[PDB]
Image (cartoon, rainbow, N blue to C red):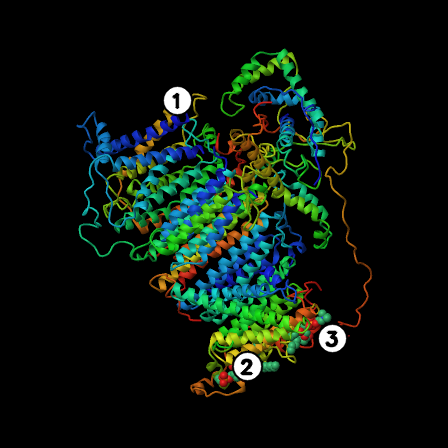
Amino acid sequence: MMTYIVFILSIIFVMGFVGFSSKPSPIYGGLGLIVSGGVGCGIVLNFGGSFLGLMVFLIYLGGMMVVFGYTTAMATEQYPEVWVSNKVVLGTFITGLLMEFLMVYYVLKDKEVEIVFKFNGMGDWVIYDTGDSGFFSEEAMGIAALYSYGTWLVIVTGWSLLIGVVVIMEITRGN
Amino acid sequence: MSLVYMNIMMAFTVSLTGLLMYRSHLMSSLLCLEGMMLSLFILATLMILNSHFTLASMMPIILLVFAACEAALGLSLLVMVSNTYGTDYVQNLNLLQC
Amino acid sequence: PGIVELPSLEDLKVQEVKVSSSVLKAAAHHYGAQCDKPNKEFMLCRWEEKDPRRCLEEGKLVNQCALEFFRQIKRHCAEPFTEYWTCIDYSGLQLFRRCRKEQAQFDKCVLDKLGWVRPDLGELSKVTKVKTDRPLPENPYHSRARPEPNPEVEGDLKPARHGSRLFFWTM
Amino acid sequence: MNLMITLLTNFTLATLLVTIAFWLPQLNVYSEKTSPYECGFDPMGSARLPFSMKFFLVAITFLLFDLEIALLLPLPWASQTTNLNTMLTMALLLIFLLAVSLAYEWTQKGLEWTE
Amino acid sequence: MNPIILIIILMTVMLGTIIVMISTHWLLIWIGFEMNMLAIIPIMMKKHNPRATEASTKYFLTQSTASMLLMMAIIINLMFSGQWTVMKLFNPMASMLMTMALAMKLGMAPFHFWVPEVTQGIPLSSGLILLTWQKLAPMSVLYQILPSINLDLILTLSILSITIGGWGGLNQTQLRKIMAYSSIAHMGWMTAVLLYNPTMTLLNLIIYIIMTSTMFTLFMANSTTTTLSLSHTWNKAPIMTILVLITLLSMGGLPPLSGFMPKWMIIQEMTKNDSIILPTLMAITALLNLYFYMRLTYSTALTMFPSTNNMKMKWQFPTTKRMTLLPTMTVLSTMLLPLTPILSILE
Amino acid sequence: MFMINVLTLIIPILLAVAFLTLVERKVLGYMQFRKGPNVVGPYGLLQPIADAIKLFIKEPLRPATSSISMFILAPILALTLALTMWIPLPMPYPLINMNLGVLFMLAMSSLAVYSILWSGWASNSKYALIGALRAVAQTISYEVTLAIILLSVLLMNGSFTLSTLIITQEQVWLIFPAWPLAMMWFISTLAETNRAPFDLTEGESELVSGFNVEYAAGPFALFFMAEYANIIMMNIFTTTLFLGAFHNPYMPELYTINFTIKSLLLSITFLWIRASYPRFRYDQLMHLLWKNFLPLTLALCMWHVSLPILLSSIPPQT
Amino acid sequence: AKTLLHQYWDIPEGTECHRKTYAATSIGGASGLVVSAYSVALKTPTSFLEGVARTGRYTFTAAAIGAIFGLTSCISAQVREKPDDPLNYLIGGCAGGLTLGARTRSYGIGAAACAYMGLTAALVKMGQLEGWKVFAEPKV
Amino acid sequence: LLQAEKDRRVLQMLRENLEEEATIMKDVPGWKVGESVFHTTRWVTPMMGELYGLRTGEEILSSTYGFIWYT
Amino acid sequence: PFFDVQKKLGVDLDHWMTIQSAEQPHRIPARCHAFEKEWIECAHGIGSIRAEKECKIEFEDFRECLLRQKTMKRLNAIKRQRDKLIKEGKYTPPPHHSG
Amino acid sequence: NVWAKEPVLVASFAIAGLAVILPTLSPYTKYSLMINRATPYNYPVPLRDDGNMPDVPSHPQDPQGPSLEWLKRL
């Protein structure tokens, strides 16, 4: 029955990600972020991405583990609040949900929405690859760049990471 | 127009407004910066896969390694802020008065 | 904008070589060896024109070459070719080391009784010259010509005219 | 969506384990079992108190080396192109830069404190 | 803060700015802005005090959100016509977001609320190097992407930036906030001329960087943060007084001194267009941003405040600091009126 | 029939966990000079079945401030992700023939860590907080080294596809081109699997079960089953990843028997390492892990980069 | 928006009244909503009721400035019938300034508002009638 | 051979689908029957809706999404 | 400024990442190779304002290669008219799965 | 001496140093380059008839062009 499945997974992503960015307690935010990263990996995987979504799932998720470690270490309230606790938190969460359901309504019962661009309402099996007899598998050769042609780029990226390491050590050392 | 682009731009704008308005936690501000990173990641990656422009799939890996080391820098700054105070609230930053 | 036209179903009647994909992958060495000499004209049409709906006549020609190849391998030697492709058919995706005795027996059949020396490595490679019937046409891109070139300002340049021609500070 | 089918079956299995835990066996007499237990005595407050931690550099260290894991992980697709020299050169340069940063923060006791 | 590591971090600031200057690929420009941010954080906190900590916090948040908004602009640019050249854009929305991200970075009037906060608590070396490079480097990018900018955006930001940098500067009895408000006013001037002839803007960049270099060198010469200390450096060091006089009148923009060649050449190649009401409004506001210079000059040299002693002790010890390059930059900043046809050195 | 294959994957893991609990108790008894469960039922077996029933009975119940959503969603995601690890595992032909499996292994292992993390936060009695941050530290340690050693051992022969890996395991096992890398990886699997307190600081006697201080008497089975599925999980992944058998071609039963025997005797070796050694230390884990494994792993990675150019052993990578 | 300031320039001058005055009220209320948004975002009025009250005061005062300006512009244009001289809008700017002084209930600020608003409004009509372009050529 | 088979198959879908369009839209005004989207005249590569439009769910689902998450 | 030490040293380090029709790593096409070859052959020796005076048509052809916006407009109109006619009940068509 | 300050670390530096040094003196990088050049992923296209090129042959059976035989030949 389903053919809008990337749009559907994107709606689940927008739900979890608005509830993420509505700022509850950051541990609930990280719950929202792991849900959002998982379904975003699902979006880019089911679009046709081979590995890069599972890659960013891994990387971005270990980053969220570090963010959990610091939000537990540094500062929490006497009682941490959840989405449905406060006036403002519940209000922003439900109005983000209302924007989501309202755009689903004004796409599914309409032709197009032009808030910033003419968005075409139908799922993205169009436009799409017409079965290229490749066997070179585009993302594999794509990340097989940065090494053959990518000379200067990995130089400045690794140099930025080395500078990042010495910068973090000297900021904590600056006492 | 590939309708999924609408919801991803919607998620970007919501993550931006969440980055801008915030109650007390700078941790949550860094967290929304991480989310905005993810939004630009997914939009650029779906762009590159619609275009089959697979020579330049450098945008995802390099954008997120750089913005993640930015987030690491912010986390160390939050370590220093919570070291030289009790908490990391937006209040008790109102010194150095303009 | 512009109009386009398509070939009707009068032109699109070429019988497919409706064998399974595994046997078609299996016999591919000698499929490229005996046949697939004239289809490089089809390939050259397809690259030098980048226009399918146009090279369909040599598509008919390569399809009848393939069907004639299968007719020749069915009518003559032999029968255990069926055993050979159903031995290569089974092992999930095709690995050419799963079944070697039957490859050797099929090769001895077709070699001692019909010919067709097997194209060894790397003979199914090796960029090819081929003569054609029509010569290669210009501008297969339906494109208009160049708008304008750049008028290159050149020549021996004079010394300056009255310094700066600002409010003052001549010389 | 076949792995989504497997995720669905495991979600149904996990929820049926929840419901067979809750609703089947016996009653639910509460009102002192819910009290927070540490080791035998009622403590002050609860958790969510500011719990100042030992390691500071180590989590950021994990983050940045996970990032260089991200740059290094396409090594098999590195190993098949006609530019062997740039391949081996930038591969050795990336791992050597990782070892250089590690060597700096190893020699400057960036791990020798509250580990 | 080992000095080898400080030379490394300064070379990375140089490297980030050169990577900005050097590429045609947009991701390299974003990498350059980011590496500039990463290395310009620990030029601050050279002291220990948490004023530098909060200033680095506020600067990091605003700088990184401007960089992420720029990445949004590039990504929407390649949602549209997909090329990695730094050229005329092919989206008005992406040009909008890109101009507003650069407006948040190099300082404009809705976006400048971090600038006196970052310059207040940090030492003078960090303040000098961030003002020079963080107001240098996106002018290169603006010079590159000028042919696709809605003029309302740049022009409104420039007008409002000049008038806010003027109106804020009258009240502060500090020094760094005076210098930061002057920076906002000069960035409004250096942005206002961009869409007409950008040689004016980049020569204004050269002259403004020479001026700010002379200013912060003359404040590295004596650890002064209030005008009280400027009066005591009147009483202890006499040539510093007349140099503060000349350079402050040169930041004012008076014609026989070399603070005039930036403004007036801009007004020339501005009013060769049909904009006259706007240059006279802008230059009346450039009359407005001169009064705090006048009261600063009054407090230094034209009047003579009472001075605390122990300067009786200090008189045996002369000015034994280090000067970066004080006299060359000074007489390049002051006596450069009649070389107005060094306009065309730039291109 | 795909639902039937789902059932023949979800049913044998349960019996695997239950009789693994039995073999834990009995091997641990015969190790410790005593005798294990011998009286009840046939020799032990129906007492782990009775343990399943016994822990079903105990009526789970909530703590004071323990927010119920996060609370009951932690061990459910634990057991769900501990099942969905076993999707691409090439028992002769796996369930989903993934084009990439080992990075999926790392992802779902990190998710198991998050499940332990969310349970330790949501249990909310300060000891679950202590144990949760101990788990966070030992995962700061053990997702760098295991992932990079993985990258090394897949660089020479694997290329992410486990069917091509079982093609590679024909002439020699991959224990011989990388044995010390394999030993460091076995240490890392024993750490990340969070059994064998040689490299585990969560179920100490210094604490009292920081992952399960007061969760609830019901889902202790869920969390328990998740960790022992982690044990079988990483031992099967070790048994596939390094060594094994050139299988009977297009014949599954011989390969399945030999693989099961190798994997389960290696799991007995794992349990026998648990039964032997004292517990470990926080700062000693950071020091030992980083400053003993990490430059040696980098050296093995660079030498396994250069070895396909020193001996032309570049893979035939599809 | 540019479209409805162009609507304010779209009326012949001339008189098509109630419409020029409604466009003036719309422009003034939009500017008042802008300034009220700034003044509620830069103050923390503490609380939301006082924020609504301050926004109501700034919007109603700026819209009343627009209303009184449009009224005296419409009446002066109907009476004296001269679209050349901007003296009608000089009177308009002074009337708006005196009513701004009335809504602030001071007299010196009101007289200065008459002077400055009258001169700037006469300048606006004067430069529009002779023709001075908005913000740019942008050519050379 | 695979190239020519794909050619005949996509030309069959294009001819039959323009006949479908010329049948199904021939009453609403506007709408030329088979004009190009583009100003030039070349063989534009189709989009899997020009080929696979209105094939009632299962066919387009097994065509455009089979390789992604099955086998 | 826009310094091209890139050009002056004679090292192409950043030009290879620029557009489509550059060297994708094995000799493959992109989705819109030919339309960029059209637009770049139109707009080389051209002063970037008569690229929009004169090379407008070919650049818009490239933009409609990328987004395929008018194609989606036409296809959506066809689907919606299909829906309204099958809602009316005028010749529920059999052409798929049959003749 | 220099060995057992941190012995597993010095052993790691030794295998790292031989990994740096040893691909310089390498008699097989040319074989890796030849094999990696001679695995075609895409179609070797034909070309226009010739201007009588006495190369790039008429049939890939003919060994005029660049063939490979050293796979079976060690």
Give the distance between the C-alpha atoms of the residues marked 2 and 3, in whole angstroms. Answer: 30 Å
Residue C15 visible in the displayed image: yes
Q: Chain of mark 2?
A: E
Q: Which residue is mark 2?
A: E294
Q: Which quadrant of the rendered structure holds the N terminus of chain C?
A: top right
Q: Is residue B51 above or below residue C122?
A: below
- SS at mark 1? helix
Q: Give coordinates of residue A39: x percent, y percent.
A: 44, 42
Give the distance between the C-alpha atoms of the residues marked 1 and 3, in whole angstroms. Answer: 98 Å
Co-location on one chain, circles 1 and 2: no
Q: Chain of mark 1?
A: F
Q: Residues within 10 Å of mark 2 (few under 14, many from 20)?
A: some
- Please give the name of the residue rendered at 67% of the width and 30% of the height, measured from the top-left corner: C126
Q: Residue furthest front?
A: G79
Q: Residues within 10 Å of mark 3 (few under 14, many from 20)?
A: few
Q: Chain of mark 3?
A: C
Quadrant in the rendering for residue I70: top right
**Relative to the observer, which residue lies in front, D48 or G4?**
G4
Residue E293 visible in the displayed image: no
Quadrant in the rendering for residue F81: top left
Q: Give coordinates of residue F121: x percent, y percent.
A: 31, 49
Residue type (three-letter) at the residue carrying disc 3 = Phe
Q: Which residue is mark 3?
A: C167
Co-location on one chain, circles 2 and 3: no
Q: Is residue A50 above or below residue A66?
A: above
Q: Which quadrant of the rendered structure holds the C terminus of chain C?
A: bottom right
Q: Which residue is mark 1?
A: F254
Q: Give coordinates of residue F110: x percent, y percent.
A: 38, 43
Q: Is residue A129 above or below residue C34?
A: below
- SS at mark 2? helix
